[PDB]
Amino acid sequence: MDDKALLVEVQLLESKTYHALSNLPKARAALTSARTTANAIYCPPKLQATLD
Amino acid sequence: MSEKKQPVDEDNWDDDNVEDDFSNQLRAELEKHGYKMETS
Amino acid sequence: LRPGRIDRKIEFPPPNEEARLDILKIHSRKMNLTRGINLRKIAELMPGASG
Amino acid sequence: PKNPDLRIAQLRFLLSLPEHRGDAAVRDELMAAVRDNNMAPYYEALCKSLDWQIDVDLLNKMKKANEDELKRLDEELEDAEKNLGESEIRDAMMAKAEYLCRIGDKEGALTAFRKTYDKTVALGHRLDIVFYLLRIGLFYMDNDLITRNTEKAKSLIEEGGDWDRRNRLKVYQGLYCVAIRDFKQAAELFLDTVSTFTSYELMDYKTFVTYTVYVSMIALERPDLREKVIKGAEILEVLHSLPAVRQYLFSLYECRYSVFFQSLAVVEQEMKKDWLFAPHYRYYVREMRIHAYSQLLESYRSLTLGYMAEAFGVGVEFIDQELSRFIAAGRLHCKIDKVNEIVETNRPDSKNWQYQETIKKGDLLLNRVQKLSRVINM
């Protein structure tokens, strides 16, 4: 899909759940992927803060 | 130079020594040992 | 460049899609590629690569 | 590839002492006979215990369906034999042989797989047959079949780039090591927790993890246990699912002796019930008890048996009897005392056992020269 803003939010949710399950490397990977998608697209303030 | 002379007179081993040690024992199967502690 | 001093002037072209696959296989020889990797598609994805 | 063949084998192993509840294992086993046309297993079960009776005439009708599969094998084989293309006959033969493998242990195995193996258009295809040969041997615990298959795949077939196959193969080699009492090699070869894929032999990645935690702690030192299992990223999610596995794995590292002893008892019942883990159930529990006893003793030179009772089970006598037997085995490296009721410590290897370590290697090393000199000396 071309709805990148939804994609960044879901990627962040995956990192949070991996951290909850204690799988740190996958959690870092979900965070890194979320950041790279977010960099190209415009970020609303809540998204940028949640990402940070 | 075969001696001969005396004929007149893991997969299935290694654990044999360990198995022999408690072959008579282990009737409790460990769970009973825990029950014995519970009674204690 | 005169032919008596230099008889041949061989030219090395940018690798063709088939050639890029061959170079990709040569440099992926030691890599543990997971099953389902498509080396052929990867050669197509980079056109006019420098090898 | 093959999907429920391992599960069927485990249920049969379960049906050795607890067959009182038929629905738990026999009812699924009856479904197993009616699925994949498993004619030889229902007959083997008939020999083992169940009469089967009316549920055997219907199975004989299924045997006629198996005969229809055999007729399909003949029809496919003859048409492929007529066909000019080579290996088409083998492709039909291997697929039908796989159906035969479900139908009968002997029928599927031996020549049916071997003839397809004899032709080798693709090394990868030949590897697939070896994997098929290895699983049936594992399911029926045919050590000789397993030894031949592992030797063939490792010696030549693994050569060539097959990363997916190498990871699948490691699980097979490790599972055999778990089946034999050589747990240490399996714990090393179960390092591929990251990429077990969803191997059919594993009931689930969750089962592979339960085996890897159980196998590793017996053969893993405390530095490795924290680095590989306690700090293991993938294992931690899987132990999140199982509370008992998490408590047992964590308690030894946390030095929670009381909780682990209770947890080990839960593990014993699971190990005896589990196929491929039942043969060494006794060795696993006692070896864990020896490792547990060594850990608390390492910290204190002097330990009151009352303190050991507080750490583990309440009864002093039960810790004392295990202590004496383990001390007798040479395990527990310590000297017990009575009336004083204090357990002391044994000499360090570096401190003075270094002399013993040189002598132990030396006695075999010297013995060799004595025999060797005579042969040339004459």
Image: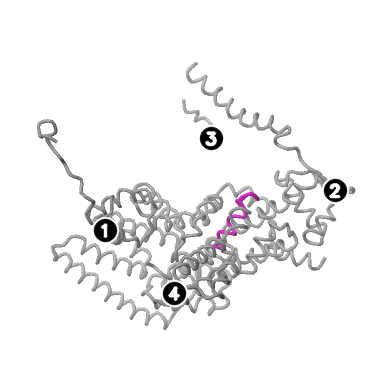
Residue range in magenta is D208-225
The residue at the point 52 percent across, 53 percent down is D186
Q: Do labels 4 and 2 share a chain?
A: no
Tell which residue pokes out farthest to the right in this image: D339
Which element is circle 1 on?
Answer: loop
Colour style of the rendered protein structure: one colour
Q: Within the image, what quadrant is residue A51 found in?
A: bottom right
Q: Residues within 10 Å of mark 3 (few under 14, many from 20)?
A: few
- Which labelled disc corresponds to residue A4? 4
- Residue marked by disc 1: C47
The amino acid beneath tag 3 is Val
- Which labelled disc corresponds to residue D342? 2
Q: Is residue D315 left or right of residue D90?
A: right
- Which labelled disc corresponds to residue B8? 3
Q: Within the image, what quadrant is residue A46 found in?
A: bottom right
Q: Does the magenta stretch include residue D232?
A: no
* Chain ID at mark 3: B
